[PDB]
Length: 58
Length: 52
Image (cartoon, rainbow over all chains, first blue to last red; front, side):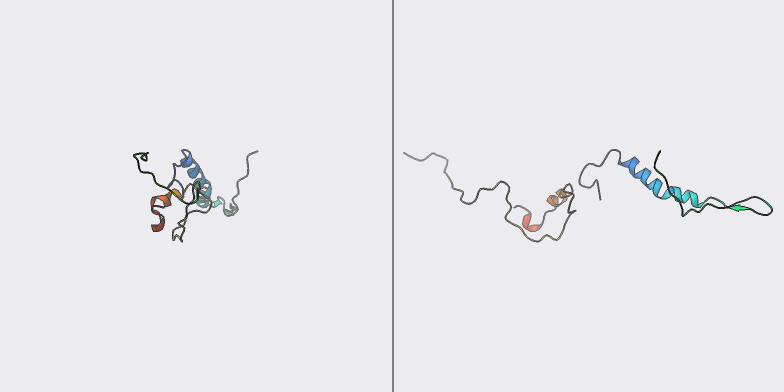
């Protein structure tokens, strides 16, 4: 949609890479985390992957 | 007495900066707001606006 009629941005590569990262790579990595269960009672902690939210820098 | 050697001509009509009278309905349309993608239509122009 862009760069086909004009010279694209020189820094668009890093921009789109960081955007794709924040969009999908974080969720993809959080999905593959295992369920921590190391005990006889098997006390299990879990991370709700759906509730993934980044916060603005302080 | 004789007129100058280059034959003179007369252009009669209205003086306009960049007027384009030949307007029709084009099938292909680009982005409404981005005027940086409208040069793609100069490249393949509509039949009627090939040499306006």
